[PDB]
Amino acid sequence: MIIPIRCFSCGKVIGDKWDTYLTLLQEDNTEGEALDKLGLQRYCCRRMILTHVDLIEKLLCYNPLSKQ
Amino acid sequence: TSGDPLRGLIQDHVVMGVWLTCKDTFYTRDEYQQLLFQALKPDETGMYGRIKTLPPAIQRPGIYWTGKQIISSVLLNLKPSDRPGLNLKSKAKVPGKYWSPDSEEGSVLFDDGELLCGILDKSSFGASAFGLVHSVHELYGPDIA
Amino acid sequence: YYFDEDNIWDLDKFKKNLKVSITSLDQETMVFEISGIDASIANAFRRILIAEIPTLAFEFVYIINNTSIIQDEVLSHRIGLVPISADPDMFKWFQHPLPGQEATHTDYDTVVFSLNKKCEFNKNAATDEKDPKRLYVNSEVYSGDLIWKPQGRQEERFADNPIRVVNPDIVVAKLRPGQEIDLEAHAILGIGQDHAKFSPVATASYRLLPTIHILSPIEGEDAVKFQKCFPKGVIELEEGPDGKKQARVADVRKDTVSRECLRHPEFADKVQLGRVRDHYLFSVESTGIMKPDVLFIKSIAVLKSKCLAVKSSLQNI
Amino acid sequence: ESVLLDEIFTVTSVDKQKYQRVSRITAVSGQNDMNLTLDINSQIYPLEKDATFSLQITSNLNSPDLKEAADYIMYGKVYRVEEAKDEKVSVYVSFGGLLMAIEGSHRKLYRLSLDHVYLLLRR
Amino acid sequence: EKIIILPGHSADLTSVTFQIQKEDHTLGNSLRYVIMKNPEVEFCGYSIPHPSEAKMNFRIQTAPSTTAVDVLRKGLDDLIDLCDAVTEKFTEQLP
Ligand SMILES: [Zn+2]
């Protein structure tokens, strides 16, 4: 679901480092190297906010309390 | 079904055996003491007051024990109360040529409990008879094997 | 019994051979060279940095209402993972509750944080744009909303430095109109060996300083190839009026042990890569808690303390 | 005195057969009736071609001649002794894996036994 | 029970097995290193029965002159002095 705070191998915090990653591909025309501007030099903490499925935004559109 | 041994040490232990028995490995005091002790682990198994070691194979200008010396050290520190030392000559698995044309490892030969020449492999200790572990089972009895 | 007579302990000679230099120090990252220290002490410093020193983290979580999508145990876990900025020695340890379990909180032991957000519909949105930041108010349950609750004396204990979350922008959960989250997290002191969320420093590790020496000096275009193999800066092509081009190792500290050369067929004769056995290159990147200076200082402090402990408990016998 | 060899030697071949460390060297000398081939730590003690030897195999390494001489010292049992092809003894000394082979015409190589050795090589 | 002597200790207290609880290689290794700098010790190696239960089997064999307890005491003092030197140089480094 949500971004896995505190990436697995290392201990860096990457919670806040997705909503500012997504608006780099979105509007900067950059490639996957965009995340390098975020301060991720290793490649353990880099296979986290690169290849993570944010599978919540497809799941939050299921409220039973829709009132509609 | 047959006589050959069915137990034995396996994959990591056997190739690291080929890397420890090999003559290219030398240990200093610290690593030798530490390794011998990790191998024995006396207290939980018990039976012994104080561990006895061998002198260093090469001494000057730095004191460096060799690996086969450590396999011999183990064979010693499990010696029964009073049983004469082991002796054995038997062919190893890794043929000698891989080491060198006319290399001497070939066949494990250790008299009086000391690995004089010959690296340990599958055959020496594993699912193969007439090696180390089998002859130790014969001489020293199974509860030692 | 053979000692080699050069392994004698001597505090003066050791202290004299030892050398330390600090390459770079910031508010988060610190890179420095220790030297004249045997491997085991480096392993111990690394361990105490990662595992042994304490730091507050959210242990318990009391939910009063949680109808969010995120599983409740998942949400408690993920809240626990966030880091908190409080100097962990301002508190005491938590005496863990054996039977007789309830009355086990005090103002020095634990600190309480609380959050509550109910995502209500935002009606000002003109069309359909499921940001959802604009369609709904209080959509994303951030970390920064975990607003600390003072417990008595604490309001003046930490008045100079409020007990706050390290990063006010971490995401903790996500909501849509109708549901709510309301909980308070009890934070206690912890020792990283039990759980990872206690460990202050994220990444603390060392490298043995690589050593590159050229046996036979290479020439010409091979100088370009050799500069090209290692990353920039560590290999200069010497301006020598004799001949045309050579290469020498400027500063290896930047280099990685990558061992690219030894694969080449022609270079393998000319260069070895070895390792200075008593030069240790630490890097320590904190997470959110403390200046890494205090991290390393308190780490050797903790080794000193554990040695004092075994020393006394021995003195008893 | 229990010194069993004091012959001088010279090196003829060195390898270096898939070992970065210890390398066997051959050092026939005397009136060429001394076929000496041994192993040495080629990491902490270098030995090259025609590098002269001073080889001494004692029994008990307790003398100031230890410190004065013996710029390199080993230790190990001698497992096999044979009389082959002649009144000619070939001796094989082990050194904890490191092997040896020394041939004499039963002379100058007399007292070699089946015990521990303490070889001393002083360059 | 932080440090308890296991029941194999020779009466002379020349070959004792310390058993430090709630500890792993972190102190075992460095303490072994500092002890091996001590000449009068013959054997000092550390182990762990099972990493799940945090018990570190130590072991020291000593020379007949000094018993092993005094050896461990001096070794621990020496390790403390080592940390003292490290913190001295370190805190000298930055302002
Ligand atoms: Zn990571």
Image (cartoon, coloured by chain):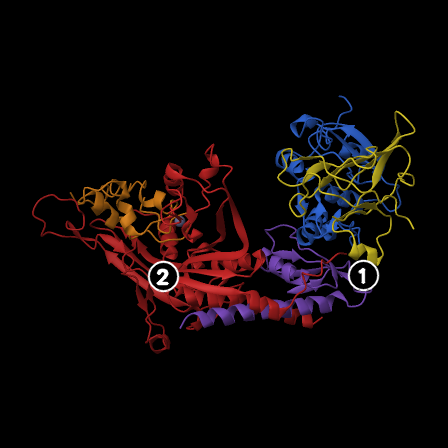
Q: Out of E41 and D65, give the one closest to the viewer.
A: D65
Tell me if residue A51 comes above or below residue C285 in the rendering: above
Q: Residue D33: image x %, image y %? A: 84, 32
Along the line of sight, the residue nearer the viewer: B104 or D55: D55
**Image hue for chain E:** purple
**In the displayed structure, does residue C123 sit left or right of residue C100?**
left
Percent coordinates x, y for residue C57 in the rendering: 41, 61
Considering every residue shown, the one lying at the far front of the view is C242
Q: Which residue is mark 2?
A: C28
- Which chain is yellow in the rendering? D
Residue carrying label 1: E10
User: What chain does mark 2 sit on?
Assistant: C
Disc number placed over residue A54 in the picture, else none: none
Question: For the view shown, which residue lies furthest in the left direction?
Answer: C126
Q: Position of residue B77 (x, y in %)?
A: 79, 47
Contact (Cβ within 8 Å) of mark 2 with mark 1: no
- Placement of the N terminus of chain C among the 4 image quadrants: bottom right
CA distance separating discs 2 and 1? 52 Å
Residue A14 visible here: yes
Chain letter, colour blue = B
Three-letter residue code for mark 1? Ser
Amino acid beneath label 2: Glu
Q: What is chain C's hue in the picture?
A: red
Q: Is mark 1 within 8 Å of ligand 1?
A: no
Position of E22 with respect to A63 (left or right) is: right
Residue C309 visible to the viewer: no
Left of D27 or right of it: where is A31? left
